[PDB]
Image (cartoon, rainbow, N blue to C red):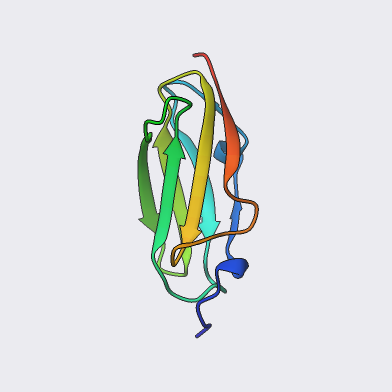
Length: 98
C-alpha cells in the first residue's frame, strides 16, 4: 500500500508520441507505486476543445487510455494525479491529417 505521490506516476505508449486525426490512439498511465487519487486526463485541441477520452482501470493501478483526436494540429495532453501534474506533463501531441 503506497502513499499518494504524483511524482511516481509513469506514462508511455504510442498515443503520447503521434496521432492521426480520426484514428484511435492509446497509451498507458501507471499509478501502481503512486498511491490512490483521482486521475485526470485532458487532451486539448489547438482550438481549446477536449478530445473524446476513455479510461480503463486494470485494478493493479495501471490504466489504459483511449482517445480519438478529430483535428489535425497540435494537442496539449494534460495528466494530473490528485490535482497535481505528473512528471513530463503537460506535453504536446502532434495530430497528423488522416
